Length: 530
Length: 61
Ligand SMILES: *[C@@H]1O[C@H](CO[C@@H]2O[C@@H](C)[C@@H](O)[C@@H](O)[C@@H]2O)[C@@H](O[C@@H]2O[C@H](CO)[C@@H](O[C@@H]3O[C@H](CO)[C@@H](O)[C@H](O)[C@@H]3O)[C@H](O)[C@H]2NC(C)=O)[C@H](O)[C@H]1NC(C)=O
Ligand SMILES: *[C@@H]1O[C@H](CO)[C@@H](O)[C@H](O)[C@H]1NC(C)=O
Image (tube, rainbow over all chains, first blue to last red; front, side, top):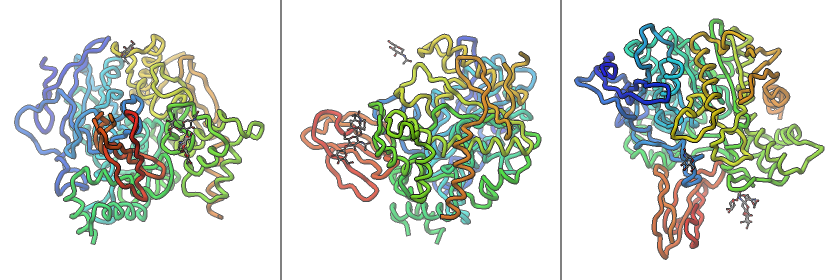
């Protein structure tokens, strides 16, 4: 087709058409948007791709950004589905465009995907991130980029030009700029761009809301299971300098210029080998190189910006899965494994609290134990398992998200909030984990419509129902299917949200309201005094 | 013996360690990320925990 041929500012591309149950879609995979950040460019902000002669093969996905590969459970789908599915390279700055067939005539609203993976991992080519069903079912344009992770993306020596930090967020921003100047070529409207992301991806989205040079690049935000003000999401200049300096000692590196010049000579693998060493304490849901608060990309801490900010003109969609915490516990909490039901003792519970809430006084830990113990059933193993799941999930996800949603809604933004309560029938993680971190994604992209996968019929319907909610938000800033159950905005007072499962929309109140008061109001007062 | 094999940046494959032992390198303290699996029995450290074994197959999991 002449529809698989498109010209962008830098040259010509050759796409591929993709089959789906509802009809074909045109795909353009692995378009370069930056000069490859190797050699003397490692650690630097990205430079725009220079114009090319000829036709770029955009039929297949490009290299995954150099990263650690999670090998907790060899051969297990639950962990491997998140692993790199293409060879690793430092030359990894490529993006992907999905557009309807035939190409729309009126400019259609654009959806941009930013993946998560704790800023240490992730890739735009993972199966669970397939643009094809969403573009076919709702006729929007879908874009997704690769951005640098781990040390390559987030190692900072704050104040230096050789390693300023945050360069993976700058990768995201360069791709957004590319969208402004090229998305018309595919039928997309640059005046209607909605950012969406999960986990670190959602944290990323939130940081674009708080960094003015990004505000001209999009109009709406969806944050799934993540928030910039999460305790894992940012790090200070002090810590970031300590962590990068530790790493340089491990790989043998003697002046900030000399230090990075030395670092740039080390093979990528030698750097990944040492990434996990630099983590300060014992913890789950903590990662070595994350965005730094340096005064540049963020002019202050995410919390101070959220509190001060003006958000009139904004529509934001926020949400969380039913069991945010459970996935992470098997990474070190005593008694937890995916290979049994992890019916822990109370002694394990108390030890696990110290792990899922790093860096706090002994007093603060007793406060957590206080709030999360059922004193009618202080020793019941199943309940102690669910409770530590909640501790980790609340601290890291539900309560940062809830606080963000309340501050935005009170300061201009129009906010809609959900809890995703459906456990996928194909889920490979055990049942005690429930609906874990990142398991709403496969439905948002409508992966159940894929024939070669074993989803039920009600789930196919559910997925299409969800794709409609997300597409309605991108077009209008309102997920509501006009007209006739309705999804109300979230406000700080009434705190209304909706459950997303096979049953119809149900409206509830308070996103874990009692817990969030402990984490957001009381705990800070305690630590500020002890 | 048939044991798993991989680095920090490669997927886990099966290999024939034979009469040697196996190992599972991991971060000692949480998060206990696996950093390696292979043949032999190498020293660990403060941050690196090594677990050795001899049998049966796939024992370094
Ligand atoms: C549910 O699973 C957890 C994790 O165990 C893991 O899964 C099992 C199926 C086995 O394959 C285990 O090898 C695997 O680690 C069990 O918790 C673990 O229990 C064992 C003892 O039963 C602990 O080992 C001890 O460690 C202490 C020191 O901490 C030593 O003094 C002892 O000599 C002994 O080696 C192990 O630490 C622990 N794993 C951790 C750290 O989480 C749990 O027992 C199991 N529940 C069941 C059987 O229903
Ligand atoms: C679907 O289920 C069948 C059961 O026999 C299995 O053979 C096949 O591999 C499954 N496909 C998946 C997991 O997508």
